[PDB]
Image (cartoon, coloured by chain):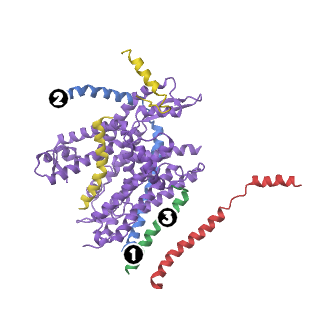
Chain colours: A blue, B purple, C green, D red, E yellow
Amino acid sequence: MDQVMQFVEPSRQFVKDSIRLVKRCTKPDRKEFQKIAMATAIGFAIMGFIGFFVKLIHIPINNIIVG
Amino acid sequence: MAIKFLEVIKPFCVILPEIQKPERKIQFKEKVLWTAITLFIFLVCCQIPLFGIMSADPFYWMRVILASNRGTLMELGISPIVTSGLIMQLLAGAKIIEVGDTPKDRALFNGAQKLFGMIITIGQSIVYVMTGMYGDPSEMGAGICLLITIQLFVAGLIVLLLDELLQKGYGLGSGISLFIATNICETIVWKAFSPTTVNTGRGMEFEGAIIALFHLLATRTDKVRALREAFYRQNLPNLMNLIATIFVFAVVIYFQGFRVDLPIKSARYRGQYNTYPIKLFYTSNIPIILQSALVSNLYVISQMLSARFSGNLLVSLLGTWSAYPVGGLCYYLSPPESFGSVLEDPVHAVVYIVFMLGSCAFFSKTWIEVSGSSAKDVAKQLKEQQMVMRGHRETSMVHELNRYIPTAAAFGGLCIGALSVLADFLGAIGSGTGILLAVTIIYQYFEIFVKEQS
Amino acid sequence: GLKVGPVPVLVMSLLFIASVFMLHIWGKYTRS
Amino acid sequence: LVKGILPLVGMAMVPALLGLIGYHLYRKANRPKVSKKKLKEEKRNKSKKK
Amino acid sequence: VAKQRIRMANEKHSKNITQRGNVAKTSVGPWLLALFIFVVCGSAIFQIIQSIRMGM
């Protein structure tokens, strides 16, 4: 149990370190955040549908290719 | 030692073909098109069934194809290639494998890892045929087994070339990263809108959550009863599962932006300002991959050990198998099945959550040294670039990075674990790790678009 | 190790996909 | 031979003919534009011959 | 440090005349390194074993 008490002192300090890192890092703004949200949404739908259709077409083909 | 191996393997390496360099930069309309053709050809190949599949109950493999991907030409898929890449990186971090800095040595190193992945594919295919999972090897016949192995081997080889072409610059990004993202997004759309109807014993129901809602509403006179079923139907994909997924995307986008940027300047030329960015998720998805791998590895050993020596007390103590470990340390490692179970046994839930966060954080920091992304490696890389920090001596720069790099890696491991645990409890479709890959790849492509608009 | 142009890679890929369909149809006809 | 092989010749000849036409079209498209600079050099030699 | 070592290294460098342009320029936790190795290797081997188990 001695090791656990020794660990506590490192436990607190790095928690302090995390707070400093949060302050320094850039934080995405709301207005730019909207722009990313549209860009990801459009790409997500466009790319996903391509998978959706190709899967649908294959199912009848599977029946013909193998009884 | 490894360099001595590299020359020995050098005749072997030469055989593997390499994609041509793009002669000139490609304009945007062309830039997009090359990727799209690659995407379709891979997508179609993934669903093609195999030949000589044999199968008691004929038409078994027929029913299998229409459900999951089991039995398709691309079954091996990307798993062989990635394993080759990760192992090679680990050896370099260990330093057991030595890679020459000179370009020719590095090119040989790339050739070697591609070859090593090829070896993995052959072994994996041979094991499946021997195991008779498709069918009895004797029944298949020597000719059929050889052909089936040939089909998989070419499937792996073609994938390597397609990925290389994207890296070469004909198509933006890397092929493998896009392919992994594609299926993940495809899964989300398929569950939402799939029209297939599967017959449960009580009644047949539509797979698609949105389709299910419309059908259920009309069929049932009592709207309230139908509405509750659609939102909270356990057996089939819920309406709530989608809403959880959308919420998870919003969080990933906001956090992904987080980064710290350090001013840098080119020594040779004045007035040139550039920033070197260190991302909050600096480690990326690697920590979760390692932690999950360890838990699965322990589970397989523990269950196997129980069968061979059921009597031994030690095997029971670590885990008791009913396969799900009901009790023991392995049981504690297992995620809680349901929210109600967590309330029933709070101590079990707390232990799993605390372990999950700790394991990811510790792995991330250790990974950096073997990865080769440590502050010491970063500083030397800048020197070859001839770009140095502004206002500080070269030696001082290493200390300056060390202030930020270690803290970021530890926090990143904790954050990635936190999302992964969060995803399951909400029940959003798809793994949290998959969600990060989709947003990251899409956003990188978006950045490329911005310059083009100019 | 020969350097290969991107378009040649595309045509080689398509031929492999075509071959698999041919083999399945040939399998049914040879059986029948 | 005719009853067993004829279906195979139909499946094999069509790709072969498409490849042959593609090769012809590729060869015609790959006709290299005579460098106008070498033509200018011929013009420069034409002034020396006059 | 013993002063006697000044002369000791001087004679060594004198030997270099014979070893021209070939003179020797000079003169990660163990537990962690083993730990990672089984994790990466184990995942590949165990995935193969698990696939056979699942079919069986």
Please give the chain letter of the residue carrying mark 2: A
The type of residue carrying mark 2 is Met
- Residue B324, can we see it? no
Question: Could you tell me which residue is drawn at 19 percent across and 53 percent down?
Answer: B304
Q: Separation of disc 3 and disc 2 at Cα? A: 66 Å
Instruction: Give the vertical position of B368 relative to A8 (above or below).
Output: below
Give the structural element (helix, strand or loop) at label 3.
helix
Mark 1 and mark 3: Cα distance apart in space: 20 Å
In the rendered structure, the answer to whether residue B306 lies left or right of residue B134 reads: left
Q: Read off the chain for label 1.
A: C
User: Residue D40 location in percent, x, y?
Assistant: 79, 53
Marks 1 and 3 on same chain:
yes
Residue kind at label 3, given as amino acid type: Leu
Disc 2 target residue: A1
Parent chain of label 3: C
**Residue E44 locus on image (x, y percent):** 31, 51
Residue situated in front as seen by the camera: B453 or B413? B413
Q: For residue C27, which numbered disc appears in the image?
A: 1
Q: How far apart are marks 2 and 1 (CA)?
A: 71 Å
Tell me the element at label 1.
helix
Residue at 58% across / 45% down in the picture?
A: B453
Kindly indicate the quadrant of the structure image that contains residue B360.
top left
E55 sits to left or right of B95: left
Quarter of the picture containing the N terminus of chain B is top left
- Determine if marks 3 and 2 fall on one subunit: no
Name the residue beneath numbered marker 3.
C14
E15 or C25: which is nearer to us?
Answer: E15
Find numbered disc 2 in the image and state the secondary structure of the residue it sits on.
loop
